[PDB]
Image (tube, rainbow, N blue to C red; front, side):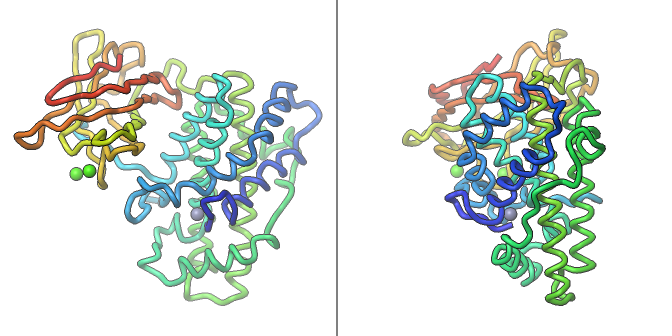
Length: 359
Ligand SMILES: [Ca+2]
Ligand SMILES: [Ca+2]
Ligand SMILES: [Zn+2]
């Protein structure tokens, strides 16, 4: 969907409507903690809206925004991101910041998660039809943006004590829940591309396509916010006693001169049993740029590990030329199974072929 960096436009309409939908649908028996956190969320409507548009303006964005796409049908290196994995990453960060009362930052992250959900609920994104593949990509989003006011909805159809919402709370595994919830909306979106929204179809078809995918984006966003309010009100932990199949690193590089690096970068772990795994951190684009925030996903060789089995974690640099760079990370977070399990301020130089321990 379109958005503008000042937190306006289609993306902003979707999250704003998301909150309003939820206010309308919330049943009488909702816990008081949930209503209070909803009030905190509304105190932070600006950041919700800003985060819902920011990813399109992020200087660190991938060149073709590859991670804003996801097809719902289709261990020595890091794994790339998709619209679906970003929803999960930003949701964990949001829950993490919420638990410590950092509500402005939490709500921004929440908004970012919702940017990615909103995208996978377009027709073009879950169909993988880019602006390069089709003139209709931009045309359709502009058509929707111009008409966004007429596609606003103010209820999901049902109160929060009813099926659509209670089904959202049934699965305490947030990540598994989110993936299949998003999957359902993205299949309807991809279906709408082929049935109504592509350049093969008519203006009436586009109108119907916008009506349905915008309604779905708003209803689905309401559901995510609902899940979020329950999660942070109960301190729900979605990772509890689950095998760590993979780790996600979220690394903020300092904005200081020459803080970034082009040297080889590795993330690594050592278990209680003395076993190690190391991966190179190397995303498609230009990693570890001064002031950027990079995301890496690492798949574990051993699929039967609990988080507490991971005793040590480090990052390690290796000079690419005869002149060792220096790299200065501001902070690194490590996420396992939907929970931030390490939040390490660094703010110090890693000079040549040095290792820095993050746990
Ligand atoms: Ca590379
Ligand atoms: Ca670079
Ligand atoms: Zn968008």
